[PDB]
Length: 162
Length: 161
Image 1 (cartoon, rainbow over the protein chains, first blue to last red):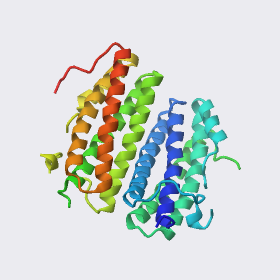
Image 2: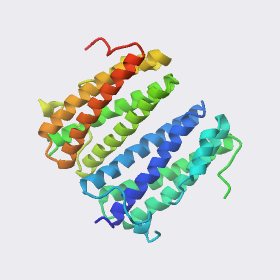
Image 3: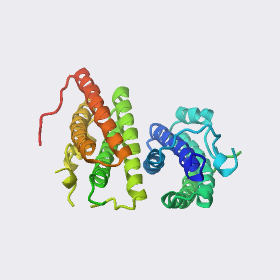
Image 4: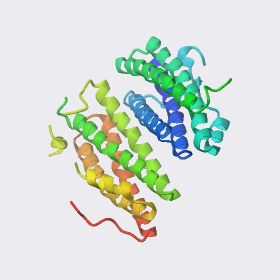
C-alpha cells in the first residue's frame, strides 16, 4: 500500500540519500584531501545505488515517489539528520580542511538521522529485501560514524555542537 | 527466470552503467570546464540511479547479479577497455573533455543497442519502460555530446573496435 512502512521508508530514505550524495559532490570539489575525497566517493556510490534500489521498488510496485503525507508519517512522526539549505550553502563556501571538517560534521549528523530511520524500517517494514537493506544501513552508517569521528579528531575537530 | 532477457539486461546494463559512472568521476577530476563537468554529473547521477533500480529488481526477484557470458540473452557493446579508462585518467582540460565525449558517445551507442534488445525481449513492464526511456535519453545525450565535441573542434573518435 501507498501508506505502508515499506513505501514510506523507500520515499523518505530516497530523499535522505539524495542529500548525502549532493554533500559528497560538494566536498569533493572543495578539498584535495584523499581520505575525505575517498569517503565522499564511497558514500555517494553506496547511497546513490541504494536510492536507485528503493526508487526501483516504488516503480515496480506502481507507487508514487512523492507522497502528500509528511515525511516520517509511516513511523508515526509526521527529517532526522537532514542538513538545512544554509548548511549546504556554507559547505560550498569552505575550502580544504575547513570543508573536510564541516562535511564530516554534517555527515555524522546525517548518518545519525539515517540510522534512526533505518531502525524504523527494521521494526515496521514487511518486504524482506527492504528490511535487510535497512539493517545493513544501520551497520554501515554506524561504522562510518566511528570512522568520521577519527577523521575529525585527526583534523583537530569533533562532531558538530548543537 | 535467471536466463530471461529481463534478468540478463539487468545484469549486463548494470555493469555497463557502472563504467559510465566511473568515467564521469574520472573526467570531473581532469578538467575544470563547467559544461563537461555538468554533463558528467548528469550521466553519473542518471546511470547510478538506473543501475540501483536494476540491481534492486534482481535482489527483490532473488536472482544472482552474476551469470553465461554477457549478452547471450540477446543473440559488451560500447564498453571501454581498461587501457582506454587509464588513458582518460592521464589527460587534462580540453583533451580530457574531448576524449571523454568520444568514449561516452561510443559507450551510449552500445548502451542504446542493448536497451533496444530489452525493448524487444523484456517481459517485465517497468523494465521494458526503463529500456525504452534509455533508448531516447541516451540518443539525445549523444546528440548533445556531438555539439560539445564541435564546440571543442573535435568529432566522434576514430573507430578503434
